[PDB]
Image (cartoon, rainbow, N blue to C red; front, top):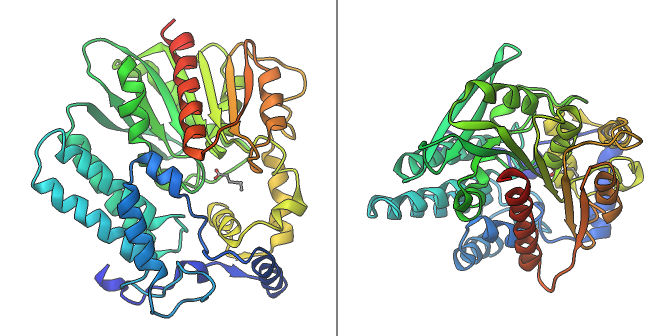
Length: 402
Ligand SMILES: CCCCCC(=O)O
Protein backbone atom coordinates (compact mmCIF):
# COMPACT_ATOMS: atom_id res chain seq x y z
CA UNK A 1 0.00 0.00 0.00
CA UNK A 2 2.85 2.43 0.78
CA UNK A 3 3.57 2.74 -2.96
CA UNK A 4 -0.13 3.59 -3.44
CA UNK A 5 -0.76 6.59 -1.17
CA UNK A 6 -2.16 8.50 -4.15
CA UNK A 7 -3.64 5.64 -6.19
CA UNK A 8 -6.29 6.45 -8.81
CA UNK A 9 -9.77 6.23 -7.29
CA UNK A 10 -12.01 3.27 -8.18
CA UNK A 11 -14.92 5.17 -9.73
CA UNK A 12 -12.51 7.05 -12.04
CA UNK A 13 -10.63 4.05 -13.39
CA UNK A 14 -12.81 2.89 -16.25
CA UNK A 15 -12.50 4.92 -19.44
CA UNK A 16 -15.72 5.69 -21.29
CA UNK A 17 -16.28 7.22 -24.72
CA UNK A 18 -17.60 10.80 -24.41
CA UNK A 19 -21.06 9.77 -25.70
CA UNK A 20 -21.07 7.05 -23.06
CA UNK A 21 -19.98 9.50 -20.34
CA UNK A 22 -23.05 11.55 -21.19
CA UNK A 23 -25.22 8.45 -20.65
CA UNK A 24 -23.54 7.80 -17.26
CA UNK A 25 -24.40 11.36 -16.21
CA UNK A 26 -28.05 10.71 -17.17
CA UNK A 27 -28.07 7.51 -15.07
CA UNK A 28 -26.45 9.22 -12.05
CA UNK A 29 -28.88 12.15 -12.25
CA UNK A 30 -31.90 9.84 -12.53
CA UNK A 31 -31.01 7.42 -9.71
CA UNK A 32 -29.46 9.99 -7.32
CA UNK A 33 -27.65 7.25 -5.37
CA UNK A 34 -25.39 8.26 -2.43
CA UNK A 35 -22.82 5.57 -3.17
CA UNK A 36 -20.81 4.59 -6.25
CA UNK A 37 -20.63 0.96 -5.14
CA UNK A 38 -23.79 -1.04 -4.72
CA UNK A 39 -23.82 -1.50 -0.94
CA UNK A 40 -24.39 -5.11 0.14
CA UNK A 41 -24.83 -4.53 3.91
CA UNK A 42 -27.03 -7.59 4.53
CA UNK A 43 -24.95 -9.82 2.21
CA UNK A 44 -21.72 -8.90 3.97
CA UNK A 45 -23.27 -9.55 7.41
CA UNK A 46 -24.60 -12.90 6.15
CA UNK A 47 -21.05 -13.69 4.97
CA UNK A 48 -19.70 -12.88 8.44
CA UNK A 49 -19.01 -9.16 8.89
CA UNK A 50 -20.18 -7.83 12.24
CA UNK A 51 -23.02 -5.30 11.73
CA UNK A 52 -21.66 -2.83 14.31
CA UNK A 53 -18.11 -2.79 12.87
CA UNK A 54 -19.50 -2.48 9.34
CA UNK A 55 -21.48 0.61 10.34
CA UNK A 56 -18.36 2.06 12.01
CA UNK A 57 -16.46 1.45 8.74
CA UNK A 58 -19.21 2.90 6.56
CA UNK A 59 -19.58 5.90 8.88
CA UNK A 60 -15.86 6.75 8.67
CA UNK A 61 -16.23 6.51 4.86
CA UNK A 62 -19.40 8.58 4.60
CA UNK A 63 -18.30 11.15 7.26
CA UNK A 64 -15.01 11.93 5.60
CA UNK A 65 -14.07 15.53 4.80
CA UNK A 66 -11.50 14.37 2.27
CA UNK A 67 -11.93 15.13 -1.42
CA UNK A 68 -14.10 12.76 -3.42
CA UNK A 69 -14.05 11.96 -7.14
CA UNK A 70 -17.76 12.77 -6.97
CA UNK A 71 -19.16 14.29 -3.80
CA UNK A 72 -22.56 12.68 -4.50
CA UNK A 73 -20.85 9.31 -4.03
CA UNK A 74 -19.74 8.94 -0.40
CA UNK A 75 -17.39 6.00 -1.07
CA UNK A 76 -15.17 7.90 -3.54
CA UNK A 77 -12.67 9.61 -1.23
CA UNK A 78 -9.50 9.76 -3.32
CA UNK A 79 -6.24 8.13 -2.21
CA UNK A 80 -5.19 5.62 0.44
CA UNK A 81 -6.07 7.37 3.71
CA UNK A 82 -8.95 8.15 6.09
CA UNK A 83 -12.33 8.03 4.36
CA UNK A 84 -11.14 5.92 1.42
CA UNK A 85 -13.18 2.73 0.90
CA UNK A 86 -10.18 0.39 0.57
CA UNK A 87 -8.36 2.14 3.43
CA UNK A 88 -11.22 1.92 5.91
CA UNK A 89 -12.11 -1.70 5.11
CA UNK A 90 -8.48 -2.77 5.25
CA UNK A 91 -8.26 -1.14 8.69
CA UNK A 92 -11.01 -3.45 9.92
CA UNK A 93 -9.22 -6.40 8.32
CA UNK A 94 -6.01 -5.54 10.15
CA UNK A 95 -7.90 -5.29 13.45
CA UNK A 96 -9.19 -8.81 13.01
CA UNK A 97 -5.71 -9.93 11.98
CA UNK A 98 -4.44 -8.30 15.24
CA UNK A 99 -7.02 -10.00 17.47
CA UNK A 100 -6.09 -13.24 15.66
CA UNK A 101 -2.57 -13.22 17.14
CA UNK A 102 -4.05 -13.05 20.65
CA UNK A 103 -6.39 -15.95 20.03
CA UNK A 104 -5.57 -19.60 19.34
CA UNK A 105 -7.23 -22.39 17.34
CA UNK A 106 -10.99 -22.12 16.79
CA UNK A 107 -10.99 -18.37 17.43
CA UNK A 108 -7.72 -17.36 15.78
CA UNK A 109 -8.91 -19.23 12.65
CA UNK A 110 -12.25 -17.48 12.62
CA UNK A 111 -10.67 -14.09 13.19
CA UNK A 112 -8.50 -14.59 10.13
CA UNK A 113 -11.52 -15.62 8.01
CA UNK A 114 -13.22 -12.42 9.21
CA UNK A 115 -10.10 -10.52 8.15
CA UNK A 116 -10.11 -12.15 4.71
CA UNK A 117 -13.67 -11.03 4.19
CA UNK A 118 -12.90 -7.45 5.22
CA UNK A 119 -10.01 -7.37 2.75
CA UNK A 120 -12.25 -8.77 -0.02
CA UNK A 121 -14.84 -6.07 0.64
CA UNK A 122 -11.99 -3.50 0.66
CA UNK A 123 -11.26 -4.51 -2.93
CA UNK A 124 -14.90 -4.84 -4.00
CA UNK A 125 -15.88 -4.66 -6.77
CA UNK A 126 -12.41 -5.81 -7.89
CA UNK A 127 -11.80 -3.66 -10.96
CA UNK A 128 -8.68 -4.99 -12.67
CA UNK A 129 -6.81 -1.71 -12.91
CA UNK A 130 -7.52 -0.87 -9.25
CA UNK A 131 -4.18 -0.74 -7.41
CA UNK A 132 -5.75 -0.51 -3.95
CA UNK A 133 -8.07 -3.40 -4.75
CA UNK A 134 -5.30 -5.61 -6.14
CA UNK A 135 -3.42 -5.24 -2.87
CA UNK A 136 -6.63 -5.88 -0.88
CA UNK A 137 -7.16 -9.09 -2.88
CA UNK A 138 -3.61 -10.18 -1.99
CA UNK A 139 -4.39 -9.71 1.71
CA UNK A 140 -7.72 -11.42 1.33
CA UNK A 141 -5.94 -14.46 -0.12
CA UNK A 142 -3.08 -14.57 2.40
CA UNK A 143 -5.55 -14.20 5.28
CA UNK A 144 -7.72 -17.06 3.98
CA UNK A 145 -4.83 -19.53 3.84
CA UNK A 146 -3.62 -18.48 7.29
CA UNK A 147 -7.15 -19.05 8.61
CA UNK A 148 -7.29 -22.39 6.76
CA UNK A 149 -3.98 -23.45 8.30
CA UNK A 150 -5.33 -22.63 11.76
CA UNK A 151 -8.67 -24.34 11.27
CA UNK A 152 -9.50 -27.76 12.64
CA UNK A 153 -11.07 -28.27 9.19
CA UNK A 154 -9.04 -29.20 6.15
CA UNK A 155 -8.55 -26.73 3.31
CA UNK A 156 -6.41 -27.58 0.30
CA UNK A 157 -5.52 -25.20 -2.51
CA UNK A 158 -5.59 -27.11 -5.82
CA UNK A 159 -3.91 -26.07 -9.08
CA UNK A 160 -5.50 -27.77 -12.06
CA UNK A 161 -3.85 -27.39 -15.48
CA UNK A 162 -6.14 -26.16 -18.26
CA UNK A 163 -5.11 -24.22 -21.39
CA UNK A 164 -1.47 -23.47 -20.42
CA UNK A 165 -2.50 -21.88 -17.14
CA UNK A 166 -3.78 -23.47 -13.94
CA UNK A 167 -7.22 -23.20 -12.38
CA UNK A 168 -6.86 -22.38 -8.67
CA UNK A 169 -9.54 -23.92 -6.46
CA UNK A 170 -10.05 -24.35 -2.71
CA UNK A 171 -11.19 -27.72 -1.36
CA UNK A 172 -12.72 -27.54 2.12
CA UNK A 173 -13.06 -30.86 3.94
CA UNK A 174 -14.43 -31.75 7.40
CA UNK A 175 -11.86 -34.54 7.51
CA UNK A 176 -10.18 -37.07 5.26
CA UNK A 177 -11.52 -40.16 7.08
CA UNK A 178 -13.41 -41.31 3.99
CA UNK A 179 -14.17 -39.85 0.54
CA UNK A 180 -16.84 -37.16 1.00
CA UNK A 181 -19.62 -35.84 -1.24
CA UNK A 182 -18.65 -32.48 -2.71
CA UNK A 183 -20.22 -29.34 -4.08
CA UNK A 184 -18.43 -27.09 -6.55
CA UNK A 185 -19.39 -23.50 -5.74
CA UNK A 186 -19.04 -20.23 -7.66
CA UNK A 187 -20.21 -16.69 -6.79
CA UNK A 188 -20.75 -13.80 -9.21
CA UNK A 189 -18.50 -11.35 -11.08
CA UNK A 190 -17.82 -9.07 -8.07
CA UNK A 191 -17.13 -11.74 -5.46
CA UNK A 192 -13.97 -13.73 -4.77
CA UNK A 193 -14.02 -17.50 -4.22
CA UNK A 194 -12.81 -16.92 -0.67
CA UNK A 195 -16.05 -15.05 0.24
CA UNK A 196 -18.05 -18.19 1.12
CA UNK A 197 -16.37 -19.68 4.19
CA UNK A 198 -19.65 -19.62 6.15
CA UNK A 199 -21.39 -21.62 3.41
CA UNK A 200 -19.06 -24.49 4.34
CA UNK A 201 -18.69 -23.80 8.09
CA UNK A 202 -22.33 -23.26 9.01
CA UNK A 203 -24.09 -25.45 6.43
CA UNK A 204 -22.21 -27.93 4.24
CA UNK A 205 -19.78 -29.12 6.93
CA UNK A 206 -22.57 -30.32 9.23
CA UNK A 207 -23.30 -32.95 6.58
CA UNK A 208 -19.66 -33.73 5.80
CA UNK A 209 -20.19 -32.21 2.35
CA UNK A 210 -16.90 -30.86 1.01
CA UNK A 211 -16.91 -27.44 -0.61
CA UNK A 212 -14.77 -26.72 -3.64
CA UNK A 213 -14.69 -23.03 -4.53
CA UNK A 214 -13.89 -21.78 -8.03
CA UNK A 215 -13.66 -18.33 -9.64
CA UNK A 216 -15.57 -17.77 -12.91
CA UNK A 217 -13.36 -16.86 -15.91
CA UNK A 218 -11.98 -13.24 -15.60
CA UNK A 219 -12.60 -13.27 -11.84
CA UNK A 220 -9.95 -13.57 -9.10
CA UNK A 221 -7.56 -16.51 -9.54
CA UNK A 222 -9.19 -17.06 -12.93
CA UNK A 223 -8.40 -13.52 -14.08
CA UNK A 224 -6.21 -14.85 -16.89
CA UNK A 225 -9.06 -16.96 -18.32
CA UNK A 226 -11.14 -14.84 -20.71
CA UNK A 227 -14.89 -14.79 -20.23
CA UNK A 228 -16.23 -16.44 -23.38
CA UNK A 229 -19.59 -17.90 -24.36
CA UNK A 230 -18.36 -21.22 -22.96
CA UNK A 231 -18.08 -19.74 -19.47
CA UNK A 232 -18.65 -23.07 -17.69
CA UNK A 233 -15.27 -24.08 -19.16
CA UNK A 234 -13.25 -24.04 -15.93
CA UNK A 235 -15.88 -25.84 -13.87
CA UNK A 236 -16.01 -28.68 -16.39
CA UNK A 237 -12.25 -29.07 -16.08
CA UNK A 238 -12.50 -28.96 -12.29
CA UNK A 239 -15.27 -31.58 -12.51
CA UNK A 240 -13.16 -33.81 -14.75
CA UNK A 241 -10.29 -33.42 -12.30
CA UNK A 242 -12.29 -34.82 -9.33
CA UNK A 243 -11.57 -38.36 -10.60
CA UNK A 244 -7.92 -37.89 -9.66
CA UNK A 245 -8.80 -36.39 -6.29
CA UNK A 246 -9.30 -39.23 -3.81
CA UNK A 247 -10.49 -36.92 -1.00
CA UNK A 248 -13.84 -36.53 -2.79
CA UNK A 249 -16.48 -39.07 -3.83
CA UNK A 250 -16.74 -38.18 -7.52
CA UNK A 251 -19.98 -40.14 -7.77
CA UNK A 252 -21.62 -37.64 -5.38
CA UNK A 253 -20.96 -34.17 -6.85
CA UNK A 254 -23.26 -31.16 -6.67
CA UNK A 255 -23.19 -27.51 -7.71
CA UNK A 256 -24.09 -24.22 -5.98
CA UNK A 257 -24.07 -21.03 -8.07
CA UNK A 258 -24.80 -17.48 -6.90
CA UNK A 259 -25.45 -14.65 -9.37
CA UNK A 260 -23.57 -15.20 -12.64
CA UNK A 261 -21.98 -18.19 -10.93
CA UNK A 262 -25.46 -19.68 -11.28
CA UNK A 263 -25.47 -19.51 -15.08
CA UNK A 264 -22.30 -21.56 -15.17
CA UNK A 265 -23.71 -24.30 -12.94
CA UNK A 266 -26.90 -24.60 -15.02
CA UNK A 267 -24.83 -24.74 -18.16
CA UNK A 268 -22.75 -27.45 -16.61
CA UNK A 269 -25.85 -29.33 -15.43
CA UNK A 270 -26.90 -29.71 -19.06
CA UNK A 271 -23.40 -30.56 -20.27
CA UNK A 272 -22.61 -33.25 -17.70
CA UNK A 273 -25.85 -34.98 -16.79
CA UNK A 274 -24.29 -38.06 -15.16
CA UNK A 275 -21.43 -36.52 -13.22
CA UNK A 276 -23.66 -33.80 -11.74
CA UNK A 277 -26.11 -35.16 -9.15
CA UNK A 278 -27.66 -31.86 -8.00
CA UNK A 279 -27.61 -28.14 -8.76
CA UNK A 280 -28.83 -25.12 -6.79
CA UNK A 281 -28.69 -21.51 -7.93
CA UNK A 282 -29.59 -18.22 -6.22
CA UNK A 283 -30.06 -14.83 -7.89
CA UNK A 284 -28.73 -16.00 -11.28
CA UNK A 285 -29.09 -13.77 -14.40
CA UNK A 286 -30.38 -16.65 -16.54
CA UNK A 287 -31.83 -14.67 -19.42
CA UNK A 288 -33.97 -11.59 -18.82
CA UNK A 289 -31.41 -8.90 -17.96
CA UNK A 290 -28.83 -10.17 -20.48
CA UNK A 291 -31.41 -10.00 -23.24
CA UNK A 292 -32.55 -6.47 -22.32
CA UNK A 293 -30.11 -3.87 -23.80
CA UNK A 294 -32.33 -1.00 -22.68
CA UNK A 295 -32.08 -2.24 -19.08
CA UNK A 296 -28.32 -2.79 -19.30
CA UNK A 297 -27.85 0.79 -20.50
CA UNK A 298 -29.64 2.07 -17.38
CA UNK A 299 -27.60 0.15 -14.78
CA UNK A 300 -25.52 2.00 -12.15
CA UNK A 301 -21.94 2.74 -13.21
CA UNK A 302 -20.51 0.13 -10.81
CA UNK A 303 -22.08 -2.71 -12.81
CA UNK A 304 -20.91 -1.35 -16.15
CA UNK A 305 -17.42 -0.86 -14.64
CA UNK A 306 -17.32 -4.48 -13.44
CA UNK A 307 -18.50 -5.67 -16.87
CA UNK A 308 -15.88 -3.60 -18.71
CA UNK A 309 -13.20 -5.02 -16.42
CA UNK A 310 -14.18 -8.69 -16.72
CA UNK A 311 -14.45 -8.29 -20.49
CA UNK A 312 -11.01 -6.68 -20.59
CA UNK A 313 -12.29 -3.55 -22.29
CA UNK A 314 -9.82 -0.67 -22.54
CA UNK A 315 -12.45 1.95 -23.21
CA UNK A 316 -16.18 1.47 -22.98
CA UNK A 317 -19.01 2.09 -25.36
CA UNK A 318 -22.13 1.29 -23.31
CA UNK A 319 -24.39 0.73 -26.31
CA UNK A 320 -22.00 -1.82 -27.75
CA UNK A 321 -21.41 -3.49 -24.36
CA UNK A 322 -25.18 -3.82 -23.83
CA UNK A 323 -25.70 -5.49 -27.21
CA UNK A 324 -22.82 -7.88 -26.63
CA UNK A 325 -24.05 -9.38 -23.35
CA UNK A 326 -27.17 -10.90 -24.98
CA UNK A 327 -24.95 -13.88 -25.84
CA UNK A 328 -24.74 -14.83 -22.15
CA UNK A 329 -28.41 -15.75 -21.83
CA UNK A 330 -28.85 -19.52 -21.47
CA UNK A 331 -31.96 -19.20 -23.62
CA UNK A 332 -30.01 -17.38 -26.34
CA UNK A 333 -27.42 -20.17 -26.13
CA UNK A 334 -30.14 -22.82 -26.62
CA UNK A 335 -30.13 -24.55 -23.24
CA UNK A 336 -33.69 -23.62 -22.33
CA UNK A 337 -35.78 -24.69 -25.33
CA UNK A 338 -36.36 -28.45 -25.56
CA UNK A 339 -33.74 -30.68 -23.94
CA UNK A 340 -34.35 -31.73 -20.35
CA UNK A 341 -31.61 -32.55 -17.87
CA UNK A 342 -31.58 -35.52 -15.48
CA UNK A 343 -29.98 -33.13 -12.96
CA UNK A 344 -32.51 -31.83 -10.46
CA UNK A 345 -32.00 -28.06 -10.31
CA UNK A 346 -33.46 -25.90 -7.56
CA UNK A 347 -33.58 -22.35 -8.86
CA UNK A 348 -34.33 -19.51 -6.47
CA UNK A 349 -34.20 -15.77 -6.27
CA UNK A 350 -35.64 -13.21 -3.87
CA UNK A 351 -38.97 -11.57 -4.71
CA UNK A 352 -38.43 -8.62 -7.01
CA UNK A 353 -34.81 -9.37 -7.83
CA UNK A 354 -34.54 -7.42 -11.10
CA UNK A 355 -31.36 -9.34 -11.93
CA UNK A 356 -33.05 -12.72 -11.42
CA UNK A 357 -36.78 -12.71 -12.18
CA UNK A 358 -39.03 -15.62 -11.23
CA UNK A 359 -39.57 -16.12 -14.98
CA UNK A 360 -35.84 -16.83 -15.35
CA UNK A 361 -35.94 -19.48 -12.62
CA UNK A 362 -39.18 -20.97 -13.95
CA UNK A 363 -37.47 -21.61 -17.29
CA UNK A 364 -34.57 -23.42 -15.67
CA UNK A 365 -36.85 -25.45 -13.41
CA UNK A 366 -39.02 -26.75 -16.20
CA UNK A 367 -36.06 -28.14 -18.13
CA UNK A 368 -34.83 -30.08 -15.10
CA UNK A 369 -36.06 -33.50 -14.01
CA UNK A 370 -37.55 -33.06 -10.54
CA UNK A 371 -36.48 -29.41 -10.84
CA UNK A 372 -38.12 -26.51 -9.02
CA UNK A 373 -38.20 -22.72 -9.06
CA UNK A 374 -38.97 -20.55 -6.04
CA UNK A 375 -39.78 -16.88 -5.52
CA UNK A 376 -38.54 -16.27 -2.01
CA UNK A 377 -40.89 -13.96 -0.12
CA UNK A 378 -39.79 -12.63 3.25
CA UNK A 379 -40.12 -9.65 5.61
CA UNK A 380 -36.37 -9.04 5.61
CA UNK A 381 -33.62 -9.72 3.10
CA UNK A 382 -31.67 -11.75 5.68
CA UNK A 383 -34.65 -14.00 6.18
CA UNK A 384 -34.80 -14.47 2.40
CA UNK A 385 -31.12 -15.38 2.28
CA UNK A 386 -31.50 -17.78 5.20
CA UNK A 387 -34.63 -19.49 3.79
CA UNK A 388 -32.91 -19.84 0.41
CA UNK A 389 -29.87 -21.45 1.97
CA UNK A 390 -31.99 -23.78 4.09
CA UNK A 391 -33.79 -24.98 0.93
CA UNK A 392 -30.40 -25.38 -0.74
CA UNK A 393 -28.93 -27.65 1.90
CA UNK A 394 -32.13 -29.76 1.98
CA UNK A 395 -31.89 -30.20 -1.78
CA UNK A 396 -28.27 -31.30 -1.44
CA UNK A 397 -29.12 -33.48 1.53
CA UNK A 398 -31.83 -35.20 -0.54
CA UNK A 399 -29.95 -35.61 -3.81
CA UNK A 400 -26.29 -35.85 -2.75
CA UNK A 401 -26.45 -37.85 0.52
CA UNK A 402 -28.83 -40.15 -1.35
C1 LIG B 1 -25.78 -7.16 -13.66
C2 LIG B 1 -25.77 -8.59 -13.90
C3 LIG B 1 -24.46 -9.16 -14.18
C4 LIG B 1 -23.62 -9.54 -13.07
C5 LIG B 1 -24.06 -10.65 -12.21
C6 LIG B 1 -23.07 -11.07 -11.18
O1 LIG B 1 -22.81 -10.33 -10.27
O2 LIG B 1 -22.52 -12.13 -11.21
